[PDB]
Image (tube, rainbow, N blue to C red; front, side):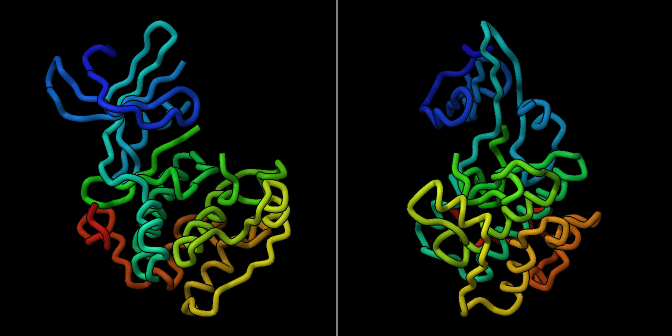
Length: 254
């Protein structure tokens, strides 16, 4: 119960409730560090998923209206401070972090869980420097059209979002924006895909195939899901067995 854990620091008033980084005192593991989400289902989901790129659930419970989740603490911080730091990622640097995520969305989906968001914010790194999907249910420049004007929904969305990430990985910012919640929205729904020149063919090919306005023909929408995507030759240097075994070295070690 909540009092087993001293509170070390607040992590985010983010979302419904709050999230504390905490340390444990009683019981088995003692003084290990943790993250404790406190909610006055996000749970349901974290409970089944057991996947090396999806944040682990350790304990759950409730009290006086308060439900407490206790997840592994993620020392890597947000992927997209690293972005903040190195401006834009090299095509490889990005193709790494992208594949991982990809096998994560892949799982999620066969378990009928679609992520909707996949901002560059709610993508956490761990001690090792790998990728861990985190916040389930803000900032729209990363979600599909077919949502913004409620349509809509299905695996598609997720993959659109995936472009935005990558695009925003290899280019300092998302594919659509501009100084306005309005015009930004508008600009998405009129999705005139402006590509850089300096992207290799493949990178561009993927994007044009991820960011397609019609979901149905968005690469990855097929019944083959993360199969199609992972298949595309942008990830041709990727050893998918090696990767899901965290035996591949991440280009940044926090």
